Amino acid sequence: PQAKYRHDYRAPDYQITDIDLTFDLDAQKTVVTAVSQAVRHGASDAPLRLNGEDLKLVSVHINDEPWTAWKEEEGALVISNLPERFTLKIINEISPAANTALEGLYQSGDALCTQCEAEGFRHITYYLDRPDVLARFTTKIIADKIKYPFLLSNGNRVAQGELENGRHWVQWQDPFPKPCYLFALVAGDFDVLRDTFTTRSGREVALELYVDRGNLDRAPWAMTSLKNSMKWDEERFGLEYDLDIYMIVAVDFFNMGAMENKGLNIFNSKYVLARTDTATDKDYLDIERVIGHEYFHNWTGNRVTCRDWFQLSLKEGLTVFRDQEFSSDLGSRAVNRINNVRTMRGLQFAEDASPMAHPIRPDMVIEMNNFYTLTVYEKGAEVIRMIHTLLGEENFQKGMQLYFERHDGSAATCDDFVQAMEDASNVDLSHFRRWYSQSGTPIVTVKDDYNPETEQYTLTISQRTPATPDQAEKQPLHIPFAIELYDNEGKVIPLQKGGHPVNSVLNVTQAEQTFVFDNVYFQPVPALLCEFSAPVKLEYKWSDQQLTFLMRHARNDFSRWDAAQSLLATYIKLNVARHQQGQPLSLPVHVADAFRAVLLDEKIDPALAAEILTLPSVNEMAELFDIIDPIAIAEVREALTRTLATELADELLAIYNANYQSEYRVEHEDIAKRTLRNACLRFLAFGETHLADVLVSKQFHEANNMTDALAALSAAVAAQLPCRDALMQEYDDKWHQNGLVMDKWFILQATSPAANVLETVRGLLQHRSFTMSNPNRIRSLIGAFAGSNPAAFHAEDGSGYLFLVEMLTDLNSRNPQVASRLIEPLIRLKRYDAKRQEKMRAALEQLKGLENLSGDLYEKITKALA
Ligand SMILES: NCCCC[C@H](N)CC(=O)O
Ligand code: NA
Ligand code: NA
Ligand code: NA
Ligand code: NA
Ligand SMILES: [Zn+2]
């Protein structure tokens, strides 16, 4: 399998302007007829090279003439001796029932549906399966009436008919030209929720949400979220929807979260279906986010698409930024920012140090589905957010307007986006472009000095990015470095120099520089890299009392939470080294006191308190170390939780009872109170055993909503309470028929700290609610074990790796994309000790040797063993 490189991009020899598709649908054998209008742009003797995979070619015509000048090659149909403009007609067969990869046209339960991003359209017919080729689609679908009463594709329904033998047909037409990755087709039987949204200029859009029969009671929240998305995009970005219909279809068998197909989004039902007894606050907020995200792609992705796949972050970074802004405007900005920072530092940083490291605009790709990454998405969004930070909102919106003005209707580049932002703002971003092309996490080192003679504060800031496996050369970036300076009383010291105000966003552009501030009347406590103003590691030698001061005084909530993270970080490192020598947890009293003060501050937003009382995850903790000891980290996380539970027991219980709510509402204040309450319950579960068992058991049985119930069950599992087995059995008994709900239970099983967790997980491969044919179940049991139980996955005997190898040996043949998700924990071997490294390398060497090794695995395994 061959690498492709960004520097090889060339404009296509041929374009296609219009394509007319006809599907004669059947699960064993679907006949596709594709009639394309084509235009040559290159040399007169260049053949047309069409992409195609696993297609049975039936015929090829050019202007109605059967064509003899062609041949098949590996992955292609090459057609020679063409005129300058012509009609290509291809007829071919495909087999949806055989498609376990879930790429192209496949079967989801009894429905037929498509997934075409990145390069799945080529599994449907021979085409220019590349996103700089944009065409107007017309799609006609013919199918059995009983099995497939609903026949959907992009755009508007323009024709309809009945045929002999219980078949029917519909035709659809989408007026906007599109790359084929945005093609969708859905056939099946559904319940439908219908609603409308009226845009700000008075267009009435019909909204339609298709779900499995019986699930209409779980549809309204998604519908509500869609309307909220449409409204927000209008208020914030000035963007309206551009068609009279918007369809969403929830399918159960899907590789990712969702897909922005124009006018016809297809969603993993996990990000659509919710009811108060089935879904958590977090589900409600995730459904909102993903609905928003796919909607926001309608402009940032569809009306302006990507010239080639190396430009993915042009749509994904910008769209992720848009979903974060949406969630933050509607909810708590502080909680959003915090959690996104947790994700960046805890998960994306690890990727940017891994063998899979790449810039947000990659230079080399073997399997493009491997690059739908935390880097491309979350670091991508951080890069967009840095642009926003440098330009300010008003200039950033001008840049948006200019990007659309220049590029609407076309496929664009990351470089085109940056250029629009520069031209609209007159801010120079030449050096800033280096964030698109350099991989890895910059390390920013800060040293300070207060001069009492001159009332000057001096910051000396340096940066460097370490080499990564993809890139030996690294250079300084344009790092927006936001600061605030606090005086003795907790008030902000105006920033200034030589009698003039200076911007609190510093431009850190060199390996090293110095900034000097005048009229610093008291020795300050700095807040550094405010709001995580650049996606970097901060190295700065804080005192605990500077950090508690920031926890008590900083003006942004984010800085308080972040000061609390810096405070724990010292003690996490300390106690990990202790654990390794057999020594128990040590924690200064004043640290415990700083958390006690948060529990009892009544001014404090309960959402902030809950974040500060949610300890860094094992993945966030692991970012603190070069070599990771996953067993020591897990045990320290537990011991710290036990220690705080004991020191704060009274305050914990009181805040728990105070935040009781009788009514359940999906509303920002209610969520915040409940999140705090359940953060208290978590500690309490790790406290005195009898009271823990009582509290947890009681919350689980009396809960009127899944958030309160799952928090209890989760706490019983995590603290291994006596009530655990009973509670777990009750939830199985009640919920076994419901896969999305069972996923949560599989996650708890997989992530259990119990000594026999691997054995329990193996047995759960036979559980009535598990199947290897469903990506959600797979991720919930197997993925959650490998990726979210690092202590068990990295058991000293290597049983964890061996289990994953067995699973991947199945999944490589069945569903390579899911396989490639699941291999990620093994790809990180170079963060572990020599003994673990040897075993992980041996596991990877077995997988390298599979017959029919997928490209997806190949790419990762090769980079890992280098
Ligand atoms: N394997 C390709 C996954 C495509 C993801 C799609 N653009 C949905 C999203 O970005 O949210
Ligand atoms: Na075209
Ligand atoms: Na798109
Ligand atoms: Na808000
Ligand atoms: Na510290
Ligand atoms: Zn996206």
Image (cartoon, rainbow, N blue to C red):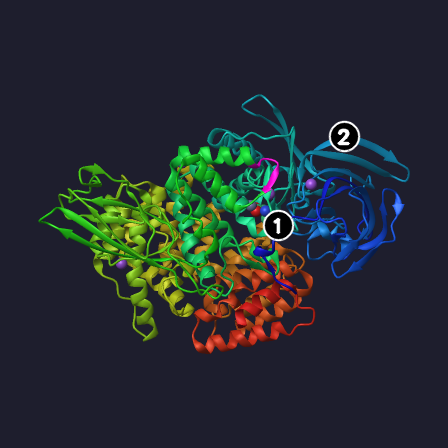
- Residue 158 numbered tag: 2
Say if mark 1 contacts mark 2, CB within 8 Å. Answer: no
Q: Image check: 676 left or right of 110?
A: left
Task: Locate the N terminus by quadrant.
Answer: bottom right
Name the residue: 64% across, 30% down. Answer: 243
In the image, is residue 249 above or below residue 679? Answer: above
- Quarter of the rendering containing residue 517: top left
Question: Residue 565: x percent and y percent?
Answer: 32, 54
Q: Residue furthest right?
A: 164
Region rendered in magenta: 407-411
Q: Residue furthest front?
A: 44
Q: Residue furthest top?
A: 202
Element on which disc 1 rests? loop
Whole-number angstrom distance, CA of label 1 to CA of label 2:
38 Å
**CB at disc 2 and ligand 2 closer than 8 Å:** no
Query: Which one is in front, 650 or 753?
Result: 753
Element on which disc 2 rests? strand
Disc 2 residue crowd, few under 14, some 14–19, many 20+, Cα 10 Å:
few
Q: Which residue is denoted by mark 1 in the rendering? A: 738
Q: Image check: 187 left or right of 841?
A: right
Name the residue: 44% across, 52% down. Answer: 435
Disc 1 residue crowd, few under 14, some 14–19, many 20+, Cα 10 Å:
few
Q: Nearer the viewer, mark 1 or mark 2?
A: 2
Q: Identify the amino acid type marked 2.
A: Val
Q: Residue furthest left?
A: 453
Q: Identify the amino acid type marked 1.
A: Asn
Query: Which one is in front, 632 or 29?
Result: 29
In the image, is residue 4 above or below residue 287? Answer: below
Query: Which one is in front, 437 or 828?
Result: 437
| Residue 592 visible in the shown view | yes
Quick one: label 1 or label 2, which is nearer the N terminus?
A: 2
